[PDB]
Image (cartoon, rainbow, N blue to C red; front, side, top):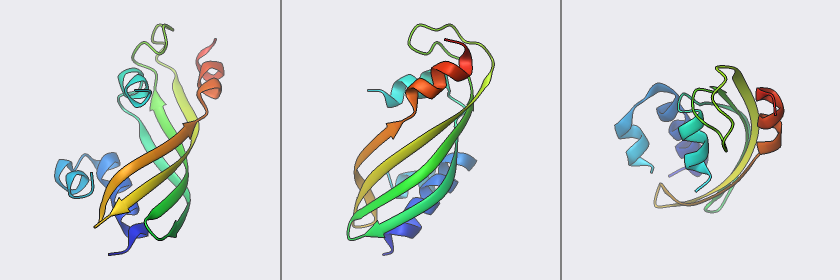
Length: 110
């Protein structure tokens, strides 16, 4: 079971809408997905070692929902996102992440 292949398939599943493949692998995340439900993930780099896998990504989406009170603008966003995943037995068990939240506020007009 290659950790680095699980991640690359989780991103594929999310960007293509495969409920099942995304479930074979399993706060502020809801703020995003409520404000940017259409978000898409572009993987720039991936580092694996043991159960931990780390990613550099850009999130692409359109601002259709209220984000932290800012009303929806319709404008697309591109937000840098770095995360860490813990994969046990081929399924993600924990996740850490830092998104460029401030860079979103610039992109939409705040």
